[PDB]
Structure formats: C-alpha cells, structure tokens
Image (cartoon, rainbow, N blue to C red):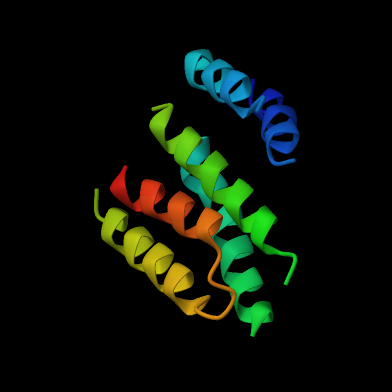
Length: 107
C-alpha cells in the first residue's frame, strides 16, 4: 500500500480527476515525509519561473489538497510556505493556480 499510492498520484498528476480523488480518499507517518516532495517541487518551480509550468502547479496543488483531505506545529510553517510560493508567481496571473491555491489554503 505504501507504493500503491504512487501510481495513483502519478496518474492523477497528469474530468476524470474526481474518480481518482474519491478512490484515493476512500482508500485510507509516510504522508509527513511525502508532502516534502511536493513542497520542494513547488518551491523549485517558483524559483525557476523568475510559462508552461502552470498546469503542473495546478495539478500538484489539486493532488496535495486531495491527499490532505483524505485524512500540530508545522501547520503554520507549511501554510506560510504555500502562501509565499503562491504570491511569488505574480507575473503569469493564472486563474487555475490561484483557485487551486485558494482551495488548498482554505482546507
């Protein structure tokens, strides 16, 4: 089960997102260290941005929100990091990434 979620995440990171999201949520430590990969990916993309990386960022934000919703001191750190990485990309001004970031921050 530890490696089974990797295939689902990779497939969903590509209208069918609702089915995979529901399956992953109903399927269920490792998440603590797993979120670091996504955090580092967003930070690297934001640093390299300063324009086709927007779909990837939106997909990563959606999968991150789905995995966190499928389920106490690092919450503020992660929230601040997400807010900073989202506010950094203030040139492209894409609505999809903003909507995904808003949903992630809300949850």
